[PDB]
Every structure is written in structure tokens, then in C-alpha cells.
Image 1 (cartoon, rainbow over the protein chains, first blue to last red):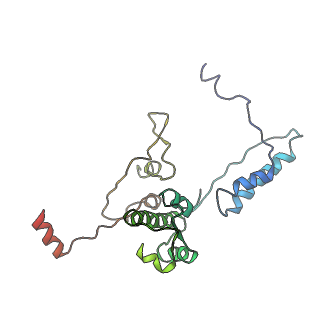
Image 2 (tube, rainbow over the protein chains, first blue to last red):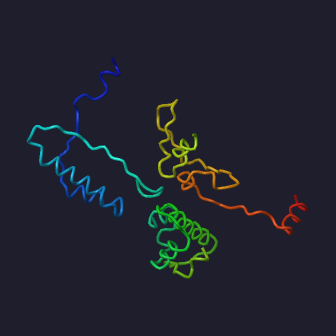
Image 3 (cartoon, rainbow over the protein chains, first blue to last red):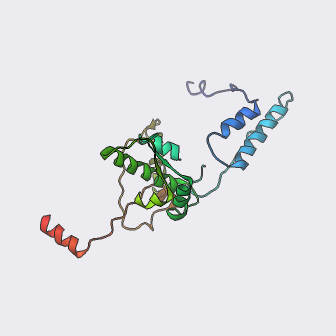
Length: 72
Length: 72
Length: 72
């Protein structure tokens, strides 16, 4: 019962964000890498556009493939 | 990479590298797709700069130009 | 393979949270001074080799073995 009341059941932190603030925070930790950052910004666009509706929310599942020193 | 390796070895404001020098370090001392080897070479420059400081001294910036790279 | 479990302990940027399977807590191994030993590089996997700084010990000449045998 102590495990069963401490995993989170329906408690979440907000998902609709300012887009340009997220863009500036992403651009100050890594150089380049435009495909990953555009994936994140398209996700936040979908989150902003859908907040009034009642549809199936499903978070992405990604794999990042590359040589051994790039910033995965 | 270079601000981190200069700050982390106490030589901040005492040593500096040029752009031709960074390009020579990339082309002649590194064969990688990632960026870890470049960080190790620039860290080697900063350690040897600290060693040279601790036995002599100078004032202002010492600028490492592209023809000073085989010294380090 | 335990070579794939050594990627977590020898990661220079990430080994301050090394998680053992016995202790369920993150443990900091980032002040430890790791020294490793090999006699060829070819049988080390490439992502594990890309974490370590390589120093080569070439082999002694005759004038060096002379002095080692006299003094030691």
C-alpha cells in the first residue's frame, strides 16, 4: 500500500509553453542540431493548438542514432 | 569547449587561442566524427599553459597563434 | 558483456550519478583517478575507447635498458 499511493496518478505539470522562450533555451546549450530542435518545437505547436479540444494525447518515442561523440 | 576548458583550469583571462589555431588542431591532431578528442586537445593546451604560468609569469593575454601549436 | 557496463562508470560527463543494481541510489565517482592498462587498443570497443585519454609507452632502447639495469 505504500508503493500504491506514491506513484503519481493524475498529477502533472503544464504543457502549453511560450515557443520562443523554448527556442532560446534550446539554443544556448548546443550548437546546430536542427532536426531535433524542430521536432520539439512542432510538438509544442501541437500542444498549443489542441488545449481546448478533448483528443488523445500521446507523447513521442524517439531513438537518436549516431557516432560516439555527438551530443546524444 | 574552449571557455569551459579555460575556466576549469584556472587560466581564465591569461591565455587565448586564435581561429587559425583551432582549425589546425581540428585538421592535424584529430580524426573524429564527434567532438571529445578536440576537447582533450584543448584541455592539454590549458594544462600546459597553467604549468608554464606556475614557473614563470606574464601579464595580459598570451595569444597562441597557429605556429605555436607544436610547442603545446 | 561487462564492456557495455563500463560505459556508465567511465563516462566523463555523466559518472557523478552511477547507479549500481544493489544500492538503488546515484553514487558519485567523479573524483576517482582512473588508470587503465592495455597492450593493444584493437580489442577495446570504440565507444569505450572514446572516453579515455591515451598515453603510449613505446618500448626501451639499448641505451635506456643500460641505465635501467645499472640504476634499478
